[PDB]
Length: 289
Length: 234
View 1 (tube, helix red, strand yellow):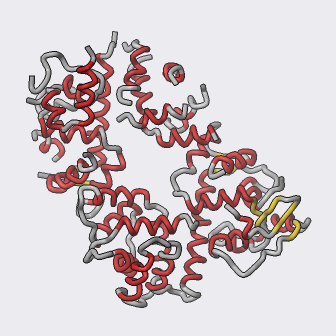
View 2 (tube, chains in turn purple, yellow):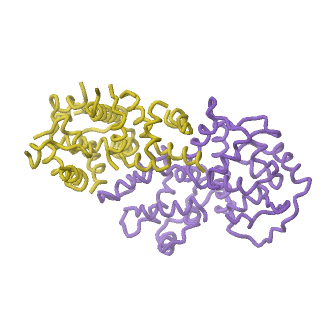
View 3 (cartoon, one colour):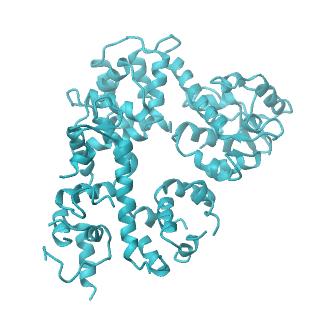
């Protein structure tokens, strides 16, 4: 919540961050910079329109924007809530904020929808959702296609950054990615198994990593699916894990990913998954701090 | 006078299903079963230590025996999503259809969260959850009807007591079952009120999140705390 760390623009004491800064805010715990905070010029606010005019509507919006954009602190919290909170509690504010007819939220209610969750000038998000002057309404469908595109963006650039630029990330690389935020007591054990008990190499793809990421972002059901076994003590073996991923998310998971997950969280289990451990790591992965 | 009421509630909450059956009962009746389910309703002085509705389609017009009681209570107390998963985790392609062995495995894992003439109906074959969830919804609709079908139908009017089914634990009947249909998918009716927070503020939530008549009998009692007892009521 001290997003001041990355904000490079200032205006009369209000600090704003460009899309580049917002991306550094999620891929970098810190960096060697001092951010050189500069007064907001009469070009940056124009560069906002410039950026959204040349940027693309897909997975690449925040990246094509580069520095041509603006993000306000409340909108930064809004975007972090998009990344961090599950895909089940945003359709409750649209229908509640657009009762006239179907769910379309006006520009004046976007500030409300932000002051609700996790709570001067127009920024990239306003200009993209409601147009250059506010004449457009934010359909819930377009906003869902936006939410998951931002998610896909962070997935792709984390893929490349942990794969160190190779087309395929290693199983040891996927292990690095999964454990990147876990700092708990068993931090050592997890890293023991990565190095002592894991068949190295073997070509995890970007589509497969996207599969695991979508599974992480649809894990609410996997919890109670797994909170069955914990109660009425009953084990969770490789077939149980496969079927539970299926019911929670409706998708196969490549055998590299499954082998990695088990070889990391078969804590003294003998082909049995320490699953509360695994869910703990997965929830460390969701909120980055 | 009322020491036995509070004692019976004590049985209804902290006692074994064996005891909750041996007191509230030799299978019970649809009138009896709701007594164990409904707190603050006494059984007669000749009650003690063995002292077309859904029920008919379990035995033969009212029969509710230990096995039926055990399994039938775990269907009004379990939510929707909690059932499907147990169904999808033991089927053998993972679509939601279970058979006698798999549905035997499902109740073991579903009942353990706590501290028979019907095997023929559901199945030999295999049963899906699209249909099972209907069995649950029917069980509820029928038991709710009976519970509020005797309280004073005189056909509801009651007013002053209707609050009391709201505080069972913790103008018609169709208006009531709709207050309980609104009332049940409630989690989002907490987040809607919590966004509206951070009395026709909600009468649209009943039509936008739950999807004016009864809205008056409730606001005269206490929102945002309303929700707590309502949720902890099932």
